[PDB]
Length: 319
Image (cartoon, rainbow, N blue to C red; front, side, top):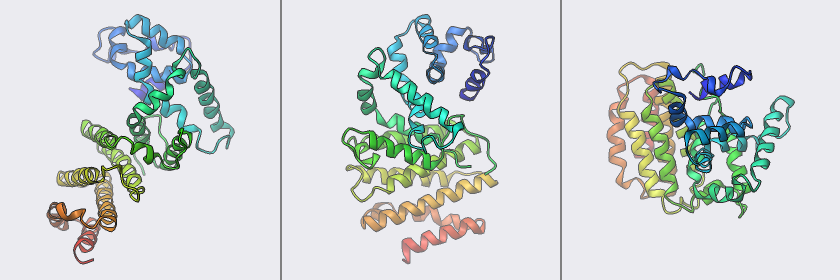
């Protein structure tokens, strides 16, 4: 639906309007029901296109608080303006126009009439939601269907995280420092990725979700020096059990996308095991048996995935 709405709005014609969208394809009876069910997706597109009069016209016809409706879509609008600041400002003419419109929209909304009075409070209050939205927009350019239209590579995501830490009031160098102020935050992103992975059944959609999960875990392990705000024990158990589960169920026939997903899962499991053992000697004392028990059946498969299993087994046992 997100791709359909943006493509419809990209036409930029008088007859091609949001009210003219063919909602009859959906089971929603009328235009009001479609607005009630998809305001989470429709509002961010109008905001980034400066259709603030349109969304206001949406608010007073749906009989809902416009302040609440715009606040609820804060993570989705943020992943549209914020990422363009930290990636090579004014590098090229074609890419600079997104930077210009993002800055213009951001500066305008900081006014008194809009959320500018308490945008900082909302930004600080619920940071996990904007983080997972930024993570989900990962897309590294092989031979897979394109993701949702808003997508940025891993390095752009890292630059955005650095910019968030840079624009923070206390001026930290790492986003994970302030994300560590609420230890329950890491709980929110991990499940949010888990719900997105479980709700879909497409092999390519699942494969990209394994990529965004891999980046978050790798980024999470990159700040293991200071600890994850007292939550290292819980996050360590959650990620390995999630990886153990994803390994447990798998189709009998392994395709190219499935093999890449399986290899990515094994590589991430190997990385977290090495990182945890190196920094915490007694980390694996309560989870070694379940890891080894799952790895043993994995050796009776294709050679390439077998090689990774033996390497992890040797590191856990021999090394």
